Structures are given as C-alpha cells and as structure tokens.
Length: 286
Length: 286
Image 1 (spheres, helix red, strand yellow):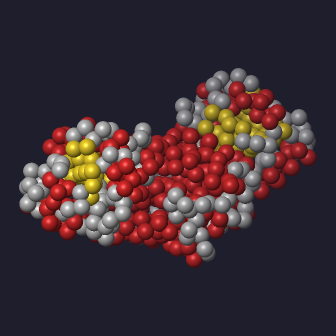
Image 2: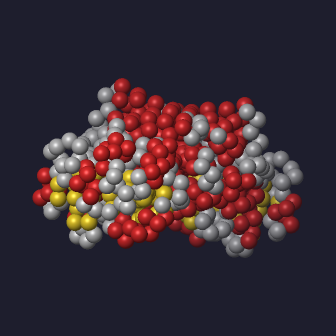
Image 3: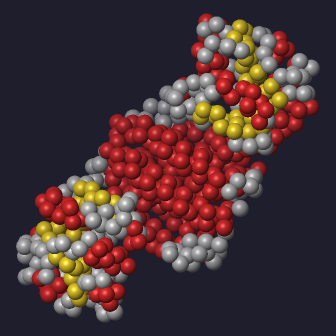
C-alpha cells in the first residue's frame, strides 16, 4: 500500500499503474500529454499534472516513458525534488541510455534501477510475468516485495544496461526460434498436419528436451572457445542443411530459412571453421 | 530376445545393433562392405555376408543403409526371402524415398515402417532417446516393445514419408533456434556474461515459458489463416527488430541474425501483411 508514482501513461505505463492500484497502492500518475489519466483515476489513481508534484508524492518513481522521450528531460524540472527518491526505469532504449540514466540519477541523489518487462501489458501483475532488473541492489532489495506485484523480479547485476541487453538478446533468440518453428510448420503443413497438432511434439517435447538440452550441453564449450569437432563438425551440419533444403523443395515449401542457415555455415567453413564444432560460428559475430 | 537383423553397419547401424545386443536379442548383422562387423561380433552378433542369409535369419529387419544407397538395391537380391518379413527403415533420405520404399516392400509381401532417429548414435538405447515412426500400424504394434529398447517409439501416421518430414521440420527449427541462441549469447557476452550463465535464464526459463508458450498460444491462429493484427502487428515487430539491430551495433556484435529476421518481415510488409499478426509470414512460404 505504499505510495507509488507512475510517470508515462502509454499502454505499458497504464498497465503498471493499474496493477499497482489492484495491489492496494496509493498511485499517483503523470503524463506529459493530457487524456490518458481518466481510466486510472476511475480505479483510484491520483492525477498530478506537474512532474514536481508527481515526484514529490512518492519515494518510488516507476518511469515508463515513450521511446522518443528521455528521463533527463521528462524528470528534469523535478531535479531538486528527486533527491532521496528512487527511479525504476522500465523503458530504456539501449544499454548506453540506461547507463547514462543511472549517472544522471546519481548526480541528483536518486537511487536507480533499470528494468525490462518480459511480457505484454495485459500480463503485468499476473502469473508468468517476469521483470529483469539491473542497477542498485539496495533499491532492488528495498522494493522487491512491491515490484513482485508486477512480476517475478530478477536482479541481474549492478551495471545499469544489463537488463536492456538481456532483453535484446532474449528477443533476438525468440524471433529466430519462431521463424524456425514457422518453417517447420509449413513443412508438416504440406502433408496436412495442423500447426496446433505439430506443437505437441515440437513444443511440448522437442523444444525443451532436444533444443534446450543441446544448448545447455554446448554452452561451456562456447566459453572455452576451442570448439573441437571430433564428435561432430560444422561441415557435417552443412550436409544436414542441404538435405533439409532438398526435402523442403520436394514438398513445395519455401527454402529461405534453411538456405540462410546454410549460408551462415558456409561463411564459417570459408573462414576455416569447417572441422570445428557448429557453435564456433558464434566467433564470426564478436 | 527375438532374433533381429541389422542391415547397414555405419555409425548409426552399429549403434542400433549394439543396443539390441544389450537388450538380449539374437542379432544378425550385414553390410555390403567388409570390416565393420568385428566390434559387434565381439558383443555376440552373428555376421551374415549374404543378404539372403541375413534377411532369412529374422522376421524383423532393421535397415540403416548409407545415404547413397537404396533399399531396393541393398535388399533386391533377397526379394523372394522378404515375403512375410518386416522392414523398419531408419535412413530414408526424403519423404518420397520412404513412400517408394513402402510400395517396394508391399510388392514383396513385406511389412514396412519408416523411422527417424532423433538422437545421435551414442544415445540410442538410453533415456531420452526418441524414434518417430510412420507406416504400418500393425508393424508398430507388433514390435513396439522391441523398438522401445532403442528409444521411445512414437507412431505419427500411416503415410510412410511422415517421419522423414517431421524430422526435417524439427531439425530446421533446431538450426534457426540455435542460431538465435548464439546471437543472444554473443550479445550478453559483449558485457562479459558467460554463455553457460546465460543459459540459466535463456533455456531454463525463457525457452519454454516464453518462446514455447507463445508458439502454443499462436498455433491455432495459423490454422485459422486470418492473422488479425489488432492486438499486435507484423509492422510493430519490425520496430522491435530495428531496436535489436541498433543495440547489437552499439555492443559491437554482428547484426546478420537480426537483419535477416527483419528482412523477412519487410517482405511480408511489402506483400501487404504489415497489419496482420507476425505469424502471417508463414504464408509467404507455402
């Protein structure tokens, strides 16, 4: 029930304020532009038009600005009032913007934690919601119980840009994995298998038990950095991808996904990694 | 303990024969070329140089030929002896080759089941081993208990090419997912996070709870085929991928993976799918 201020009332910011209201917090809401407060006010929020008033209402300042906006600007007029308060910033654009924001907050005597929301607005405050945080451990520990009302809180580290970096990484992985699933679905779909049927083997079993297990079994090899190909080489996987391409062609299914995959391996072979293990390809990318 | 013949003694074929020997079967082994039988003979296999003799030793014929070889040719000289026997073929190259093989077997009065082995040779006969099968339900049911010694047996359907199709699809998904993980790992690795550390969030949580859940939640939408973008559009995901690209560039991490992902979405936008949901992209591929 502590007081909280939510600065930024777009879709995510409004969901945050609503979830805090539903946990019994005294929520004050601010937005630069008018018209977004009414549904929250109907649920018990207090509107504050002036950022200085909004910041002054609460020690905990949950900030979810629009992508174009910046913390230093939105909260600049409240610079004096910020001393002794805490910012949890949930919409940094890049790791460098999060690191700049932490420095700005420190200058003003404000605690800072950066966080990445790992679910859409409709799932904030519900089971499965996870928020990844980076920045002050003190803030994290002081407000963990409050933050746990929004989603399971995970503290990654003290470097402010880590949460944006993890989110970027996880989302990159998501898009690649989803595109792989869609090619797979197209392939079984050419024999009449519905996608929802296919998920029984593809998601309930293959994804965790094969894909996930293989990644866990291979991750220490990446960190070691040698990639011996004794027990299976990058070259051999090129052959598998050629077979996938040919099967896709015989089924009348577009080959872009496997072709782009094979291209990547061909580049590693041309860079000398053909007798190394598959995961050596990461070394092209850093 | 029933008798079984294994035809083809490459790495996989030898693992199959060894696993059957370890379950107490009387295993007869054949290969076109000499030199591969000795380690199996040391474990109790019987060598048969003549395919007619090998086929005659057992009703259950487990066939794992080399990629270049074909069932009709390897087992052609045993055409008469094949009547009343059963072929479980574990190395068809394409769905059409499996469907040809089933027809060939039928002509000779042989039962036929095609199967795809979903683990490497070293894991055959061990927990986690899964084999996907397509073809005769009668064969599947007659020999399920024997086959379960090699891996959990799954019958997909009566069409002989389904197991090769499922395997192709699942492997396509695997390569895309692994490449996504490797880009993610490179990204967190640019801030010093080891890959093995990263798997704690990426594989133990994100992969099943986010990626998998999203695929299951979206699969019926693919089958419906309309892809309303009301609650989130293909275009909006283009913006997310632009942010991923920019973050990757700021971290000094190669942008090929996210760029290729964004390219795919740009094509769907140019085909008119921008206001549709993300998964509409599958429709470009079939």
